[PDB]
Image (cartoon, coloured by chain):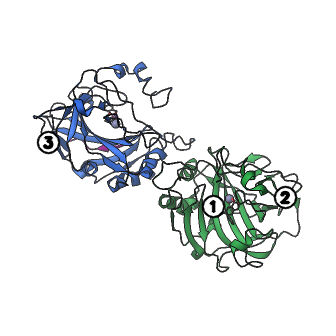
Chain colours: A blue, B green
Amino acid sequence: DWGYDDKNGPEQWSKLYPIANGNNQSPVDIKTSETKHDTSLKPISVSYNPATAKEIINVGHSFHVNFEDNDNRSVLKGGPFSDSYRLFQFHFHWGSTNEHGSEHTVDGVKYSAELHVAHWNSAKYSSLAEAASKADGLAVIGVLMKVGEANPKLQKVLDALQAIKTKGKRAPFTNFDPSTLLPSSLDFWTYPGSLTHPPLYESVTWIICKESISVSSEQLAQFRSLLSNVEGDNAVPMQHNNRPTQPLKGRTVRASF
Amino acid sequence: DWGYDDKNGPEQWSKLYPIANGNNQSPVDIKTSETKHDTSLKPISVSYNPATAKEIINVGHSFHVNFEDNDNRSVLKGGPFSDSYRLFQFHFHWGSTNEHGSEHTVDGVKYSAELHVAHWNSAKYSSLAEAASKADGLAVIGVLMKVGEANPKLQKVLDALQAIKTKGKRAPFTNFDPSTLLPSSLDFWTYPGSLTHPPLYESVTWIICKESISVSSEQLAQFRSLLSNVEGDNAVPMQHNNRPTQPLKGRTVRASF
Ligand SMILES: [O][B]1([O])O[C][C]C2=[C][C]=C([N]C(=S)[N][C]C3=[C][C]=[C][C]=[C]3)[C]=C21
Ligand SMILES: [O][B]1([O])O[C][C]C2=[C][C]=C([N]C(=S)[N][C]C3=[C][C]=[C][C]=[C]3)[C]=C21
Ligand SMILES: [Zn+2]
Ligand SMILES: [Zn+2]
């Protein structure tokens, strides 16, 4: 139905998902000379319980690490939020080559990949399903991933991918605290935005970290060696899944710093 | 340089390696109706000592498993041979899809991949460096691989690929008997031929197995997820390394069966 090829990719998504041309679409270019430093922004607080880590899935366009979200063992607080948000998933976006692959850009600079750590508002809603399409329903941390030194913090994730090479495969994925993937400093930009693929809900408060994390060209090759086809079919490696930046349409990107 | 691209591939090899146009070039199409039964052909005897297994290396166009060749712990004889031939290497050839990856063809049928188990004449010569260019220097078993069920005999080889992802990377590879990769029956065809890539020496007596072995689509994808680039550079996956069949130029393909 949708993907990242010319026939089915980001420039055609509006045919099934009209919000694709909406006014709070993500990702965006962060122009640093136009960010408002906001004094009321408190530090970001993550407290993740590695026990909430549940499984790793191949979803054909990407792979997902999902978390038990039945209670408040793993939460994000602070920043612009009064509410606690419940960890439910992390995943990555990458590009065909190392020169692009991030979704978010900073001063028009494209990075090699992007981590998304996704949370839902359990103070206001009782489920992800209820939260997912509310303006205040999702909190997502974006981390820009800069091609360089191999990132050993990625290691448990990349070692698990051999178990889920083809679309539909899943394996348990336990005892993992995704805060171990976050940069050293949680200084951040925040703007009201969307999911970066279908269903593209304008439900996301973004926390884009100013600090990047490393990844080697060979760790990126591991992502791209993952297959979009089902077991038995001809291999179609997942070459890219990064959406181009979208118009800010008058939104303000606030800095914590 | 040489490779398998439109730039440096099999159709321009003759520029740097003029023997590419020779009269004993490999691979060839084996036409079952034209093969001659030779009553002098003995059964092929392989006995390989798993302790000769030394190392696995990414050589850019392929990966090689190399064996200690200082004695005759690991030998080929029988078939058309008066001499004993010392195991030194096995490796594979594959194609960009699963339909076309073998080098030899049988009645024009292309298989998905091909195993080469390479030996040098330790009766007439004292090293590989020496034997490599002698008409009677090399003996190579070629097994055709047919896409189908996962081949569990490939498991140790495929498990080792994660340690040699980029060109020049090598790792220990020990305690392996590659006769485990051969089909049950060692009924064969034999013809005089060449190395199937540069330096393309007409030094090879081929033993082409009548029986194929299996390989899965996902095992072939693991071959193709090896990188031809050096560490640090942008990932270039190894998509194919099979040479087109060459003119038979009046050679007789003998059958053991
Ligand atoms: O990169 B992204 O698109 O946008 C950024 C945040 C994000 C978070 C999670 C996910 N993962 C899934 S399964 N998305 C589907 C979904 C999510 C919620 C409700 C219905 C449906 C994707 C994204
Ligand atoms: O498929 B093939 O080309 O041709 C078929 C047999 C074969 C055997 C070994 C190898 N592997 C190497 S390292 N080849 C290089 C070489 C150079 C000089 C002397 C020896 C060997 C390759 C082949
Ligand atoms: Zn995402
Ligand atoms: Zn070969």
Q: How crowded is the residue under tag 3: few (<14 C-alpha within 10 Å), some, or many (20+)?
A: some
Q: Helix, strand, or loop for circle 3?
A: loop
**Where is residue A200 shown, x and y percent of the image?**
33, 27
Mark positioned earlier in the residue sequence (2 or 1): 1
From this view, report whether residue A137 is shown above or below residue A101. above
**Where is residue B231 shown, x and y percent of the image?**
47, 56
Cα–Cα span, label 3 and label 2: 77 Å
Q: How crowded is the residue under tag 1: few (<14 C-alpha within 10 Å), some, or many (20+)?
A: some
Residue placed under numbered mark 3 in the picture: A43
Seen in the image, is A61 located left or right of residue B201? left
Residue visible at 25% across and 34% down in the picture: A32
Closest to the observer, B45 or A93: A93
**Tag on residue B253?**
2
Please state the quadrant of the image where ligand 2 appears.
bottom right
Seen in the image, is A129 located left or right of residue A172? left
User: Which portion, as a residue range, is magenta?
Assistant: A64-70
Chain on which label 1 sits: B
Residue B208 among magenta residues: no
Residue visible at 84% across and 61% down in the picture: B255
Amino acid at circle 3: Pro
